[PDB]
Image (tube, rainbow over all chains, first blue to last red; front, side, top):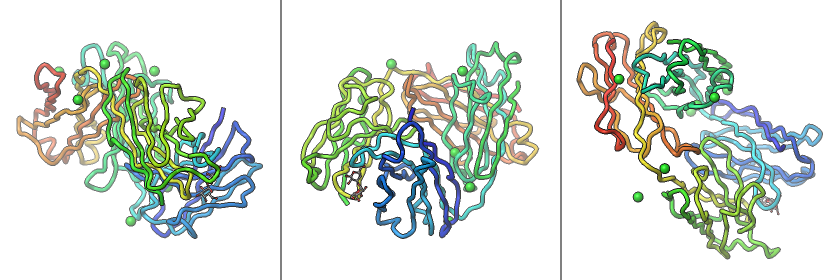
Length: 218
Length: 216
Ligand SMILES: OC[C@H]1O[C@H](O[C@@H]2[C@@H](O)[C@H](O)O[C@H](CO)[C@@H]2O)[C@H](O)[C@@H](O)[C@H]1O
Ligand SMILES: [Cl-]
Ligand SMILES: [Cl-]
Ligand SMILES: [Cl-]
Ligand SMILES: [Cl-]
Ligand SMILES: [Cl-]
Ligand SMILES: [Cl-]
Ligand SMILES: [Cl-]
């Protein structure tokens, strides 16, 4: 199975530097032309940089020429992107990808969000959305977690460490008037299972190294 | 740089019916080796892009023959013979003939389906939040279609304005529905001044506007 696992996303102020990494597996990395593309919020993909099999040819789009550096370590099956002198326009989800021929990218990483912004890092507050007669609809109950006042994106939410996925909706983050983000994650369960089954939301906000396990009770 | 222009910008389709997406380049995409390098990608909500078509008409190994690519020179078409629910999302063309490689702006494929009224849930603020000084009241609408819905907040039967925000999920990859959250934000002191908090929902699926209330 082919995997490309990226890391290093996060927040840096304008003029700063950040380093992304892309760890491959499942194919012969040394024999692959490799690529970085990015997607700005609400837009489509755009090229950033690529590197051929020996590392002898490095291409950069005009906007990042002289500020970004692409490199590879074949013995570690790793692709790197060193970003310097970052601008707000560089804010995007960055994807590493394998290029078999002429931009027809066939294997993609999971994405890494780079935010370029001067605002402070703020870890979220997690509040329960408790099930009650008012979160009942027929034979079903809704419960959730309110992940409030964090910066920057992203936060991830899972339920019972990933074992609970049916009926789950984690909403996209909302920009609040304060400039901080907020989101809710909710799950619909049979109301008969309340008081029997435990429900825990796992909130992760890496930029502030916040990992929370909040038990949501009726 | 080569300009890739896609049309339509949004395409409403019902399951089982065909769909067509066009893509135009500002230059010919014939490379000096005689091949034309045009690919199509699909981005499902909250996921990485995924390759469908390349070299104008080659289908990716994990992509069924329902998808087909066609065209020449600067005019290209992606066709889905029968649309499935998992086809929802944004589609991009990409030329690789010239450097830099350029993507289209995207075409949103939207699934039309039968009306589904929302289930409505309301949550009072938690006591942990109240200890901090602010009150959030959350109204939830789950698994509805179409997307258009009206959510009004009433505090002691007074209509609210300017103190609530909405978040809407993208159309689901399995059942093709939406979910929506509306959040009323108030100081603790303002929250403790009133008694009845109501979320009124207007949707085509409901038998009439629905209200979910609680007494603080
Ligand atoms: O060297 C010119 C060209 O290199 C990269 O695109 C190449 C493509 O030309 C080659 O034939 O195929 C590989 C696939 O492995 C790459 O897609 C750059 O992306 C491009 O900007 C240009 O610089
Ligand atoms: Cl800034
Ligand atoms: Cl987020
Ligand atoms: Cl489950
Ligand atoms: Cl960070
Ligand atoms: Cl219509
Ligand atoms: Cl239907
Ligand atoms: Cl009720």
